[PDB]
Amino acid sequence: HHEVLFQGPGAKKRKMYEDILSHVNILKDMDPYERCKVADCLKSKSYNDGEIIIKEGEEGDTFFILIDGNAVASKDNKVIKTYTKGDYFGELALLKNKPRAATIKAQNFCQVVYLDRKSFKRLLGPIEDILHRNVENYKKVLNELGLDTTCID
Ligand SMILES: Nc1nc(Cl)nc2c1ncn2[C@@H]1O[C@@H]2CO[P@](=O)(S)O[C@H]2[C@H]1O
Image (tube, rainbow, N blue to C red):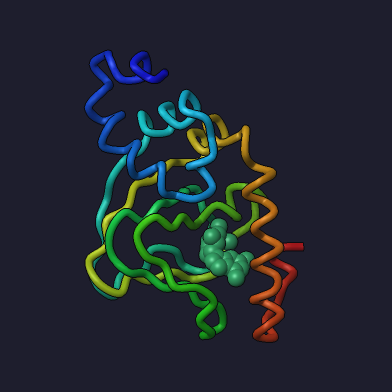
């Protein structure tokens, strides 16, 4: 039972965040304690229509979850993924310690929650492997479209 995870001061933030984390597919699968710790450390920010969230080729230190809005990822001007509420992105640079492999732009008013590298390494350590084999699905799209894949391998 979870009464223990929602009793203290931190409980308000813990609770708005938990329904949300419950629909981010790869972390909906973390168990509750681990997921409550993520909720504790999330921060919020917003992007306007047209703003760049991630610029391809830059160093990246931030992991994102989209909680509202529409954003789109492209690489060498090819659309490789559309994002909506519940999606996460920006993990690959944190896992591989390489520059951002793609650009992500807001397509309307977007609200996100995020973790920095130290928080991502600390809290999401238990699942770096599961996150990592999602990357194979990234290869397919890179290949589907004839784009460079050395950013992954
Ligand atoms: N087909 C895809 N290939 C790749 Cl390498 N990254 C993809 C793909 N689709 C989305 N992304 C995401 O765009 C982000 C760009 O900053 P990262 O740290 S490299 O993380 C990246 C991924 O989360």
